[PDB]
Amino acid sequence: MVLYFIGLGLYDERDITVKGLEIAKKCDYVFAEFYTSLMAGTTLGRIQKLIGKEIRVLSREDVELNFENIVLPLAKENDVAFLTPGDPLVATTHAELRIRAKRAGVESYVIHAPSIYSAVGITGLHIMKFGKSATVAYPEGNWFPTSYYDVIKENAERGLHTLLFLDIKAEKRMYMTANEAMELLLKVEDMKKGGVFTDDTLVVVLARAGSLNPTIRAGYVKDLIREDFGDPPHILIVPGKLHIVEAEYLVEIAGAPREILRVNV
Amino acid sequence: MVLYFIGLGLYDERDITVKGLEIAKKCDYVFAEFYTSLMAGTTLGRIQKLIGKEIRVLSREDVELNFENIVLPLAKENDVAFLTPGDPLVATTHAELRIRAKRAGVESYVIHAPSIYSAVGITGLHIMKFGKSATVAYPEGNWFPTSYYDVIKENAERGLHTLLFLDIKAEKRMYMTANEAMELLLKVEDMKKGGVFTDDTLVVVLARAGSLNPTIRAGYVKDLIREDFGDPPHILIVPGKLHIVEAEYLVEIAGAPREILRVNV
Ligand SMILES: Nc1ncnc2c1ncn2[C@@H]1O[C@H](CSCC[C@H](N)C(=O)O)[C@@H](O)[C@H]1O
Ligand SMILES: Nc1ncnc2c1ncn2[C@@H]1O[C@H](CSCC[C@H](N)C(=O)O)[C@@H](O)[C@H]1O
Image 1 (cartoon, chains in turn yellow, brown):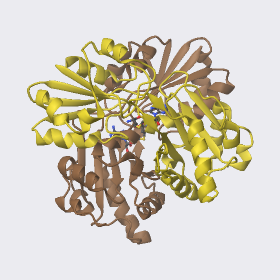
Image 2 (cartoon, each protein chain N blue to C red):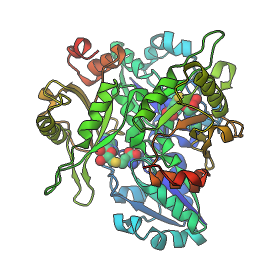
Image 3 (cartoon, chains in turn orange, cyan):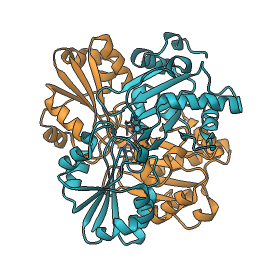
Image 4 (tube, rainbow over the protein chains, first blue to last red):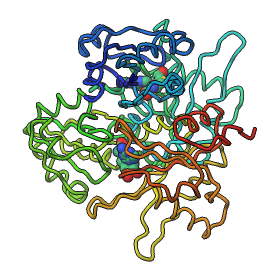
């Protein structure tokens, strides 16, 4: 009669909250999806072992299309767990699954977990200063999305930071790198020529948040465009005007050039 | 010889990540602070028990003026852990404490936890649609902070949601409620009169995120300002231009007036 949306964390199988782990163990069935995002620091098996129960993976279609046929039915007569990377209702369309639960007379509860949306706070950039967020999608066929470009422009204009989620082909297990995102923007800049993203623009790259050894680097596009930030997942941030304090943190902890202390403050 | 920054979560002691717990367990000394936020579902005793360590709680001044005197020193001889509500680097200036740890010669690591910043997802509002954030500060005497008003304004202008962190005075055990926040905003409406916040404005309130039954309400200032939302902590949200899908979740789960469904395109 109960369905729990349990967050799985950022990186590995230990980023789940204690609350989420116990509740999962008590559930009769445990489903999980791994398309919205991917747990780079662990494996389906490791996760299974930790929780103890056996996890049934759902595809994008299984969820978006037949969640009410695969999951909800059991949730009627039992206690079901739905596991998703990061935080349950973040950056995903899962929030509407709660509406379906209600429609089927099923109670749903949310168990949160760290999100990349809030873990960027490790970059020293002030959470309160983040403006509208966006996704840098891969150009395909005749489709070449460039909206993120504008999102970055409206935020910088008002002195806010822009968080750019990078593209992901969960299926193909293919991650978009910070470099590839920096490349695309340069092309969008070259087409729109608004002076929003250029070799002189300051950027921050957060790689593998959640890990004890994440990669936090700040620098000018021309200098980071070809730097190796390690294995995915990646996150690109185009900061607005920096606080002296924000800036010091990027220099002292993300190896930012001293130049930002005078040019970007 | 290191320093760990561990998040405790949103509501009770089980909101810490397994990663965080297992690390806190194997630490020599465990500091903390409960002034940046309020965990409405636990006690220092329950945390200590779960951690199996004695937690010395520091004050803002202890931290802001003596961290390198009370904490870092031990960090050179032992593994120290500094716990905090929710995520330690969200809506706090703790990130600066890392610069200290460094100049003191002390490696530091960050372990995240669910944060109110990403927990707003449960409201049904898209995470990427949130623009700049702000805090509604308690007036102190003849001083009346108004900043947050312009933040709301600036965001609604761009059709983005606004996350309003409510003030806290842990020392006095004062926890601004969503009602108090609304009341203050109305007064600021008279001051600046910009048609930013009025009896007819739609607002969303999230109370006690992290609990299995948080209070999620959406409605018009006039109908909510007098409504009881339960014990703090509270968070107030001023949505921008809704999506039909956001409107549905608000109506179906937040209990918003069905009229909001008919969006004005
Ligand atoms: N640990 C991590 N480090 C850096 N980026 C990450 C990451 N985890 C996820 N991401 C970013 O977030 C995107 C997933 S979109 C969904 C976000 C997820 N629900 C959450 O709450 O975290 C990935 O494509 C990548 O751009
Ligand atoms: N569990 C919770 N439920 C509702 N609001 C919360 C909350 N936790 C924090 N808040 C809001 O955020 C304010 C504290 S600011 C600190 C936030 C914390 N660092 C985090 O990561 O979440 C509170 O006064 C309240 O306005």
